[PDB]
Length: 85
Image (cartoon, rainbow, N blue to C red; front, side, top):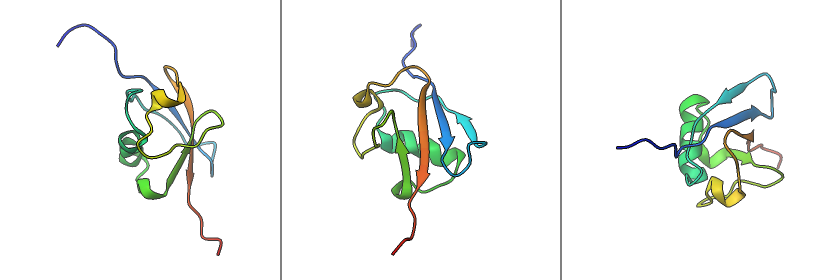
């Protein structure tokens, strides 16, 4: 509606392969649920299994980027659940 920057950039670093890098713009107030929603739009990995991690912190449900005190174009580490057993 008017001039103003709300959304904030981000950096996706695949844990399995550092070569896989993807910069995505998402609001800080955006919760990991919506943020990861985009992460799926680019990677395709189901959210329920997508384990993202901020600066030493783990991405929880309902938690917003701002909750982690992130910054414009903050670093994010992408991960995925494993079998183990």
